[PDB]
Image 1 (tube, rainbow, N blue to C red):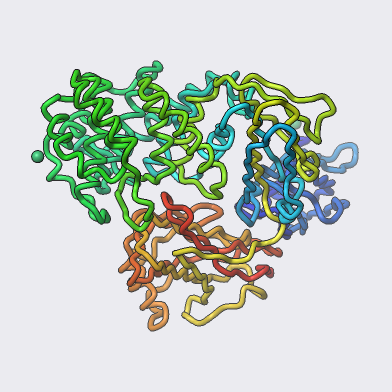
Image 2: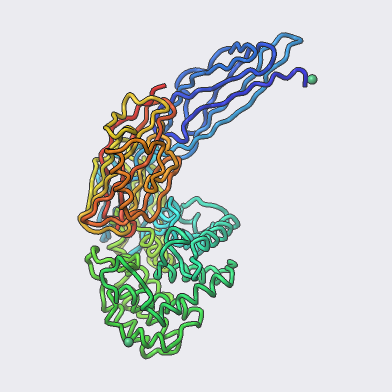
Length: 639
Ligand code: NI
Ligand code: NI
């Protein structure tokens, strides 16, 4: 070991970078030997990172000295990882000691601006042609642009879309975890590959369900019911039925679920039928309709287990007028029929398809639903229980036509649609098409989903070269090159950067170690009980893990301007708060007459030139209600 020359090499870098950012990294090299060291530092970068300058020549380091190398880096377009490598090798004379150090540093690259989609769909009569709009994809970077074309003989659903959307969802609320676990339950490596989806192996897929089932139980309240963000939170009755539906259906496939977890959950579902009075659904405009949605879903989950008492099912049925959607009437109809009351069961199923959901989104039912969600969930219940086949074709045609065009879908709607597409995946329907990306005519006996690269999409043209109507769906998703125009619908959001004192602070000419106070202001023209505030951080800004609603600040000495902002955040209905590497997340119940204030501390850390993401707010289960605020073009951090 006498020929060794230990060297300490530490890289100072951002927690993450955004696609297009440039950062000035520092490689601190220390010589803790008793003799000088001549070093050759070879720098390389892989993944979505690139070195701006060249690798440096020799490094002369005397004993005890720490030097710094300035390494300008650039983040390449896309989503994934970036890595920087250093191979330090000492250049020494015959009897002298040698340096030999290998180090690698990985940072996540995430684009500054969220993913945008384009969704088209049409029926082409024999001989008719469809071409993608030329304007349609003007905004996307070609590196990130990927599309999927679905062709069918009958009205379809793109299961590839819903699968990709549930897998991409980043937040860990109870409903979002269950929704995201349903595809990993009913799909397989073979099914996934035939759709063009590249996922994990069946063993790893089953291992993902086991870790999921445990995460859902981390949310089970001491009484047996489940809460949306924390075990300590309020009981979510309809979500307890939802989780119980999933937990029961996983056991049916062969996943182990602790018996005490199931027994306590079933005990709640039974309490919901026999005692609806104890249910407190506070943001619900119509209480009778919300309580009915719960009892009906609890009735269906209990009946699949042969645990629903007929007496309770018969009493819920006496109150069928309370229903504000056809989905709870259908769920109760399936329960009554499963429990032996086919008479009352047939009546509830008939009535279910005759009653629509109120098209006014401002009426909160607390069932995470919509017209879309309910129509999908009802198509699956009818098919699975082989009820009304004549009505299934009208419901599928309606659902097919109303689903495809929606820019934003809740997790609940994506799952509802995934389960309805799984229902019709192997549906006979002959089709012939001539496309722009293939010389040989395309044909099929069922819906065939083909993947397309950015080149194939720009010029995409599909012609029905058959004798029967053909259906097409075209879903593309990429990242925009530049920030889109700020927009808002029902919600509104604005971000102001302040100094720790309380005055305004210009994002350009910010120094490393500078502490800033980020003020988020949210208004809504309607009450939005399920609003999620996501504020993506610019790289170079690092989140101080401090909940300012509690009052925990680096300074309590400063007041007047800052003091009232903290007092305002103290008045907010915060449901959940998260301080991540690359974002500040807060789930907040917005009231129309009470504008929401959120504040968080950030520190400018790594010098560079960074893209500033726009602040966004969205209703999690009415996602047409959303806003994206204005942001400065760049954040410059100086040494
Ligand atoms: Ni030795
Ligand atoms: Ni009664």
